[PDB]
Image 1 (cartoon, rainbow over the protein chains, first blue to last red):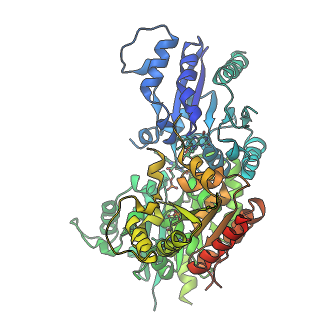
Image 2 (image 1 turned 60 degrees about the horizontal axis):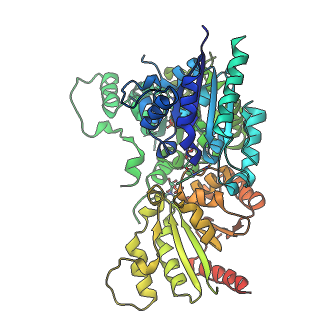
Image 3 (image 1 turned 120 degrees about the horizontal axis):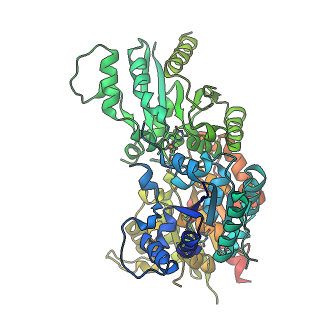
Length: 193
Length: 193
Length: 193
Ligand SMILES: Cc1cc2nc3c(=O)[nH]c(=O)nc-3n(C[C@H](O)[C@H](O)[C@H](O)COP(=O)(O)O)c2cc1C
Ligand SMILES: Cc1cc2nc3c(=O)[nH]c(=O)nc-3n(C[C@H](O)[C@H](O)[C@H](O)COP(=O)(O)O)c2cc1C
Ligand SMILES: Cc1cc2nc3c(=O)[nH]c(=O)nc-3n(C[C@H](O)[C@H](O)[C@H](O)COP(=O)(O)O)c2cc1C
C-alpha cells in the first residue's frame, strides 16, 4: 500500500482559515490522503465548502457542488455520537500521522492536561506510539508568552513525544501552512521506505 | 440507622452499559441504598428505563412503568441548575461511599486536574475525607497506556486518597461489575460496625 | 486620562449575587469604569437587570429601564462569537485591573491548568504582565479544604503573579464585596500617580 494517511486536527485559532489550503494541498499530493478533525471553535473559521472550494482550486476543477467532498469529510464532535465502530478509534487506526494545525492555547492545555472530552482530544489520547504527532501552536503573542505555555509545550514534547513546529518568532503566528505541508511531505517520504 | 448509602458515578465509557446491573444489584441488597450520578457522556450508554428494567429484573417484578424509579433517580447536570439546597452538597452529605464506575480517561483527568464544571466533579470536589471513593478506570487500552494515565492515577491515589479498582489486565477493561458490587458490600460490612 | 478601568470577572459561585453591588459601587466611584465578564454558571446567580437596578440604586436614580446599561454591559461567551476585533483582546487592552470575584473552584482549576475555552479564561490567558489580577476564591468550605485548592492557589500566585484576596476564615466565604471595592479603590489610587 503506497498511501500515506494524515489526520489534520484544526482548533480554535484564526490560523484555521488556512486549513482549507492545507487540505487542498494534501489532496493534490499524489500518494497522500487526508482526513480532518475540527474542534467546535475551529468550525467558526472555516466551513466544509471552504475545503471543497479549496480542493477544486488545487485540482483545477470548475466550480460546482458535492456531496462526497472528494472525499475529505470534516469530522466534528457531533459525528462521534451518531458493537458499532467508535470514530476516534477508527481515525487512530487509519492515521499514519497526526498534525495539529493550528493548535490553540486551549487545545495545548487540554492535551497537556490529558483532558479528552472531544473528538480531537479523544483521538490524541487514544493514539499508539506508532503514530507521530506534529503540533503547530498558533495564538496571540501574549497567550504564547504566558508562563503555562512553555510548561505545556514541555509536557507535550518530553512526556508525549509530540513534535512542535513552534510558531514564527510578536511570537505566536502559526508556521506558514506551505511549510506545514512540506513538513508533512517530508514524513510521507520517510514512510515510503 | 442500619442503612449504607452509595453514590454511583457513571462516566462516558462503554462500561456504563453495566451501570443498570450494578444499580439493580445494590437495590436488591437488603441494607444498601443507591443514588446515581451520570455525566452527559454516560447517558449515551444507558437510560433511566434501563435502570428501572434492571431493578425489576433483580427484584423479580413483572414489567410495567414508573414513575418514582423505586426510587433510584439518575441525576444529571441539568437537575442541579433547576437558600434552596444545592444538589452536589445534598449528595455529599447523603453518601457513605462514592463509586466511580466506570471512570473514563476524561473524568480521571478532570478529577486529577481539580476541574468541577459538572454535577459529578462538583460532588467529588466537595466531599469530606469522611467519605471514601472507589475509582474504576475503564478505557481503550491505548488510552490507559498513555503517559498521563499513570500520573493521574498517582494524583488521585496519593493526593486524594481515592481507592483504585484498577482495570483488568489489553489492560483497560473495567473491573467486572459483579466484582464492583461485592467490593461495595465489603464496605457496607465495614460500615455496619 | 484620569480614568481607572476595571474588568470584573464573575464565576459560578453563590457570591455572584453580590456582583451587582460591586458594579454599582464601581460605577458611582468618580474616576473608575467597570466592565463585566460572566462565566455561564455565574449568569445563574444574577442578571443584567440586577446590575442595572443596582446602578440606579447606587446613583439615586428612579426605576425605569435601559437599554445601554449606563453603560455597563455584562459580557458572556456568546458575545465573543458574534479583521474584526476579538472581544477578549479588546478587554485585555482596556483593563487596568482584572478582578475575579467570585472565583469558583472550577475557574481556579481552569486558570491553574491554563485552560481557556471561555471569554473569561481567554481574557486571563491573553493578559500582559502590565495588568494586575485579583482573585477572590469563594466556595463551599470542603471545596476550599480540598488538596488541589492550595496547589492551584500556589500556581496562580507564584507562577502567574495573581493576587489572592483569600476567603474569609468554615473557610471559603468570599471576601466581603465592600472590602473588594475598597481593595479596588486602593489600586485606583496607586494608578493615579
Ligand atoms: C475571534 C477569535 C479568535 C481567536 N484566535 C485564537 C488564536 O489565534 N489562538 C488561540 O490560542 N486562541 C484563539 N482564540 C480563543 C479560542 O478560540 C478559545 O479559547 C476556544 O474556546 C478554544 O477552543 P479549542 O480548544 O477548540 O481551540 C480566539 C477566539 C476568538 C473568539
Ligand atoms: C462510542 C464511544 C465509546 C467510548 N468509550 C470510552 C471508554 O470506554 N473509555 C474512555 O475513557 N472513553 C471512552 N470514550 C470517550 C469519552 O466518552 C469522551 O472522552 C467523553 O467526552 C468523556 O466524557 P466523561 O468525562 O463524562 O466521561 C468513548 C467515546 C465514544 C464516542
Ligand atoms: C446552586 C449552586 C451553587 C454553587 N456554588 C458554588 C460556590 O459557591 N463555589 C464554587 O466554587 N462552586 C459552586 N458551585 C459549583 C459551580 O457552579 C460549578 O462547578 C460550575 O460548573 C463552575 O463554573 P465556573 O467555572 O464558570 O465558575 C455551585 C453550583 C450550584 C449548582
